[PDB]
Amino acid sequence: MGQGGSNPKFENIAEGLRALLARSHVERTTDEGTWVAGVFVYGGSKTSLYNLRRGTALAIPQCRLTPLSRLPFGMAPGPGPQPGPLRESIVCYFMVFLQTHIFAEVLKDAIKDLVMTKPAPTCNIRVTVCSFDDGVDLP
Amino acid sequence: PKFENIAEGLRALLARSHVERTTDEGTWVAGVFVYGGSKTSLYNLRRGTALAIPQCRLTPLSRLPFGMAPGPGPQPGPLRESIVCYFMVFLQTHIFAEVLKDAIKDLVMTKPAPTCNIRVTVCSFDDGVDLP
């Protein structure tokens, strides 16, 4: 409990994940140790996502997290100096690198469940699994 | 200007296969994850991939985390970042992601370091990525 009865918001995400994840005991790492799956977390707001990320990190020793970056526009990128492909929105994302595909499915389902418990914009954070066809070699 | 010079290179290697670049759903379900090289060569390729492929969307460059420390003790931490950059190219089909991964490997292959050091993998998002 912190000074005056409360904990930093990411400390509460870390614990909430620890609980959801205590429910499923799938494997987290391989012998190969290769980074083949991930979760792409996007939307919310930069502070909702700085907070989710800082918590994923304390809750899961076994993942590696990117910084937050901005996302491009989809369907009809605005007016632009820059070519349409390169034009970036103010929606941020971050990625979690993982070594098994089921831990990625179980992580994505715990982020879904946790954020739905929180108020906007946090409840509006979206998440998707991804696999990397040749794996990523993180340095 | 390596932007159109790289674009012309992409363009001619891409030009060989003819596959679908687009779906009527419009969904962003595949990408090519490009990393390694230097900020500079990676920025240059990004600009070329943009000029060459109107049908794709690209992330800014960002920094990659550390992987696995060999042997014991010091194991890095989920949040520490390396000096190695990356970007992602979003695509509407998995096969054109196949073709652009191959086109990037072949182009940087014929190039001095650090451009020849850029690695490239294909990836998929199961529920798609709802770009803004």
Image: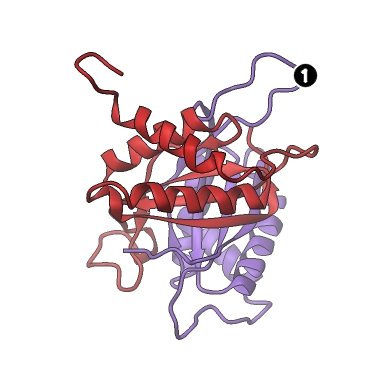
Chain colours: A red, B purple
- From what the image shows, is residue A109 above or below residue A74? above
- From what the image shows, is residue B5 above or below residue B65? below
Q: From the top left corner, tell me how far across and down residue A29 is, in percent.
A: 70, 38
Q: Amino acid at mark 1?
A: Gly
**Front in this rendered view, residue B62 or A79:** B62
- From what the image shows, is residue A109 above or below residue B54? above
- Mark 1: few, some, or many residues within 10 Å (few <14, many ≥20)? few
Q: Is residue B103 left or right of residue B8?
A: right
Q: Residue at x 42, y 53 (%)?
A: A112
**Front in this rendered view, residue B113 or A18:** A18
Q: From the top left corner, tell me how far across and down residue A15 is, in percent.
A: 43, 32
Q: Is residue A1 left or right of residue B63?
A: left
Quadrant where the N terminus of chain A sits is top left
Q: Is residue A18 left or right of residue A50?
A: right
Q: Residue furthest right?
A: A31
**Front in this rendered view, residue B124 or B115:** B124
The residue that label 1 is drawn on is B71
Q: Secondary structure at mark 1?
A: loop
Q: Residue furthest bottom?
A: B24
Q: Residue at x 60, y 63 (%)?
A: B9
Q: Is residue A33 left or right of residue A74?
A: right
Q: Residue at x 58, y 82 (%)?
A: B20
Q: Residue at x 61, y 43 (%)?
A: A98
Q: From the top left corner, tell me how far across and down residue A42 is, in percent.
A: 38, 52
Q: Is residue B1 visible?
A: no
Q: Is residue B30 visible?
A: yes
Quadrant where the C terminus of chain A sits is top right
